[PDB]
Length: 153
Ligand SMILES: [Cu+]
Ligand SMILES: [Zn+2]
Image (cartoon, rainbow, N blue to C red; front, side, top):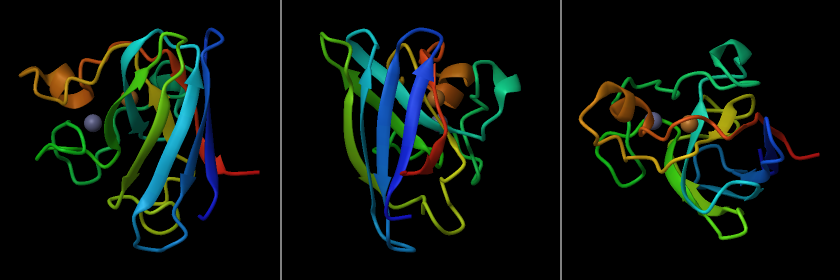
């Protein structure tokens, strides 16, 4: 779409308004956001499968993997569909996201509308930890907050 949002929220007051703009069927998306309630430091950020509560928190399915690759980040050879590596939280526990991608579509085959955008405690290990868990998740640990990607309104 040309205006999508994902309101992150967790067990605690950790919350974050993510924004996504695509417009173009096959153009570079802009993705950005601003958490409020993480700790400082790097936090893994990914599009988990779908709004699947049974996966643990309010919703957080496995790392979405349509092409069935190993985990990593935008700069890796092995990166899943929604492997937006990690973001950096401030000393005030705010991680201002601002990146762009061309794998997804927000409106098309890879409509991210409906997906489950989740933040992790630890840094994404860029799926290089040489262990399934890491090479599937980034060893980023438990999901401080979870959320769903929808239309901005
Ligand atoms: Cu994740
Ligand atoms: Zn991944």
